[PDB]
Amino acid sequence: GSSGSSGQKVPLPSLSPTMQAGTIARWEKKEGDKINEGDLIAEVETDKATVGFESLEECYMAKILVAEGTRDVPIGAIICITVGKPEDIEAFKNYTLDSSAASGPSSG
Image (cartoon, rainbow, N blue to C red):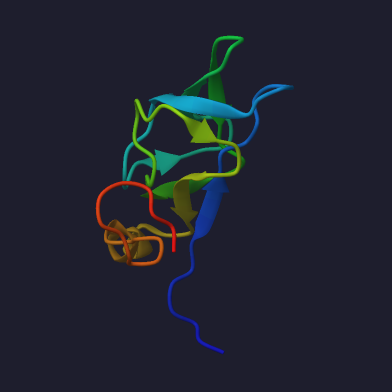
């Protein structure tokens, strides 16, 4: 078809039972920062408390769609992206979900 960008979207995983939405406490890691399985990727604030999202494996921060502090973060809402190499990060440095918006959440 078309082999261009090869990244991985990270859908805000429900770190709770009745978790409907969370808040990106902090991005323990940054863009271009190497991540290792277990290494804290970021913290999420839930009615329960501030949870810690661990990595699923080795990789690097592709893009951080949702920054830290973003409140009202729904479950599944890509929080960040991951790649297999840093040489791709750069390419992902300038990534946008469907280039189309005015001011705020639009989602065409």
